[PDB]
Amino acid sequence: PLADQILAGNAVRAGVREKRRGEEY
Amino acid sequence: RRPEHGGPPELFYDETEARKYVRNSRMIDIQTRMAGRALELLYLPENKPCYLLDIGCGTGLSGSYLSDEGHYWVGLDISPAMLDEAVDREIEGDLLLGDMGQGIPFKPGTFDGCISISAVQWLCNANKKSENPAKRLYCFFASLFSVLVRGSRAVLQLYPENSEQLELITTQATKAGFSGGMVVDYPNSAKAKKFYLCLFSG
Amino acid sequence: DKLNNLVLFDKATYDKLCKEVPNYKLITPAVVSERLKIRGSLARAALQELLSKGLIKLVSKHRAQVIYTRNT
Amino acid sequence: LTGENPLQVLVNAIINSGPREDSTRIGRAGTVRRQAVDVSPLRRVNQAIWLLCTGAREAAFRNIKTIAECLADELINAAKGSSNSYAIKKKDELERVAKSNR
Amino acid sequence: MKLLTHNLLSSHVRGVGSRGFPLRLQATEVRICPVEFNPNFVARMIPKVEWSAFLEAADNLRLIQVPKGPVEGYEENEEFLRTMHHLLLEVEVIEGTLQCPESGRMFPISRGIPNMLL
Amino acid sequence: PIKLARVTKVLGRTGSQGQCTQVRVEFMDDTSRSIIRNVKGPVREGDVLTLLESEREARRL
RNA sequence: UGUCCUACGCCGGCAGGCGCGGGUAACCCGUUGAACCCCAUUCGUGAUGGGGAUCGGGGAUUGCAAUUAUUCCCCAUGAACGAGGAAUUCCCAGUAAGUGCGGGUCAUAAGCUUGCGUUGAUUAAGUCCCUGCCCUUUGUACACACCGCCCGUCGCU
């Protein structure tokens, strides 16, 4: 839709990105 | 990392940083040899000193090099702290305080030469919303072209960090009517690589 | 600039340290050497002499720092 | 010096030397400007700690002034909010340049 | 402030370009600083410098004893060039003010360098 | 005037290098005001935030 | 790790010698007694008791041979160096950094690479802005390419 496009351009993408970094006996 | 990331030149180069700046013999050596290269760069007539606009002199070490050979100059600066440091060094040339981007306030056909020491790579970024970098560079270049004698020589020492900054400064210079080019000191080197805008009127 | 701290206690500065070290509210060799324009070795020797006189109380002992306080 | 618990002076120095607003750098092609952004309280504490560290380190660095008493003086002057602290001056410059780059 | 520096000064306002020159002067204390005497230098301001601006700047500086015309020569006059050197390069107005004709913006020279802040 | 605010949820991080965090924040003097603001550094839900001026809403691409 | 590792006794302050043992190896060096750190003194903002370069002399060690100072110990002078315009390297937990300790190269150097633990933090749990690589679509912008001008004026043989 038009308003969805306008609000997607008005907001910032976020969400998923897997960043792989980095006892008993 | 770099002095340009610290902030505006009026407030970054304060009392204590100028105090530790003047006590640096490495700075003395690099400034004297760049001043010598800049004085050798322009083809001024021998046995006849020229009227040089010294912009970005600051402490006036390049101005001290000019005064050591019998030449005369006037200094334009933006920070009062290192201006007072230059005053305390019993310097001979005159000093002016103001923003070079707002325009050089001198009559046309006055200066036979221009010496810029680490002042053109400063102005590429903006530290205020009211300051437009393209407008500021265009106004500074147009005022410098106005105040210069037709046929005078202008040298500008710089250390650009990418090719886009050089692209903007060169396109502002070539839209301001300056005729000239770029001279690099040891382009394939890293420590000894310097950049030098050379300009003239006609 | 170039400091000119004295190498031995003259009569006048000895008089001010006689009548003034009981009242600074803080005692360390650093500020004593700074404000009296005296050698720091003489400052620490003077405070060992003065604690031998016992008119300034100890707080803590360390090789690099010594700290002292008033009697009242 | 202050006659009471040094922890209160320390937390007052932490509170008073926290940069509440500063500038971020943005730019697409050569033209780089600064936008006035806000600092999280955790980063406020972190920058206050780092600024007191820089003040204590580069305060004297070349004379009889001991690092312990220099740190004590810096913490006391930051808790009092005086302009003698390097941390307070740097913080105030940070909010002022944030206000200059709204 | 050397007299040649303000004698070549203009106003940096956009609207006054380029008829803002010259600028008026006001002095409360004047210093004399020794400057090396270059005879070629003093010889080759005189065709270039504006003489009427020099007279009006001297009139704002309370001083009258100057020659009324541009003295052109082959450096054979020692005392005229010496007086010009003393007036231009050695006279310094450390404390003072500058005023623009068409904008009225003030510039306070306060120990000892004029500001140009917008 | 300096004012204190409380966040509700994070909208997401913004900036060219992802240096700032755009976050939804609201007020205690009235529980009706709601603004969007950018705060850099580590920001999680629960912290109390500080506004030097409550005039404009922060907005970046 | 070892028939070069050395325990111990004698001599010379040290560089090093002499003598007698242990070891072909978790047995002897070796409860592998190390450095940083810790406590106390002296020093005290001083190109200074910092830093040690570059020198002179003596002695000893290693070897056919040491001069172009192989190497070590001592003594004597004490240069730059006052935190580095500007380009750039590495990095997220026992990690970086400080700190010392072994193996290969060795008649004798000390200087490269590999390891070792000890003291052990700040910053972030991120982004595609710069760099590089790989995907999806495309060859529509610009460049290449086509067309046009292909610098004009006078003067003699």
Image: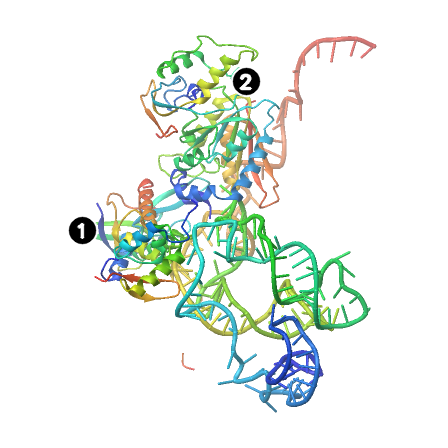
Task: Give the quadrant of the N terminus of chain F.
Answer: top left
Subunit ID for the residue under disc 1: F
Q: For the view shown, which residue lies furthest in the front direction?
A: C11
Image quarter of residue C29: bottom left
Identify the residue at image location x=42%, y=27%.
B103
Closest to the observer, G74 or B12: G74
Rendered image coloring scheme: rainbow
> As displayed, is residue C58 above or below residue B51?
below
Closest to the observer, E68 or B193: E68
Q: Secondary structure at mark 2?
A: helix
Q: Amino acid at mark 1?
A: Ser
Where in the figure is residue C61, as x and y percent of width and height?
34, 67
Where in the figure is residue G20, as x and y percent of width and height?
68, 89
Inter-mark Cα distance, 1 to 2: 80 Å
> As displayed, is residue F15 above or below residue F45?
above
Subunit ID for the residue under disc 2: E
The answer to whether one can see residue B170 in this image is no
Q: Label 1: few (<14), some or many (≥20) within 10 Å?
A: few
Image quarter of residue D13: bottom left
Q: Label 2: few (<14), some or many (≥20) within 10 Å?
A: some
> As displayed, is residue C68 above or below residue E58?
below
Residue corresponding to mark 2: E39
Where in the figure is residue A14, as x and y percent of width and height?
36, 55
- Tell me, for residue F32, which label it has, or none: 1
Where in the figure is residue G72, as x and y percent of width and height?
64, 67
Taking the image as shown, residue G43 lies to the left or right of residue C65, namely right
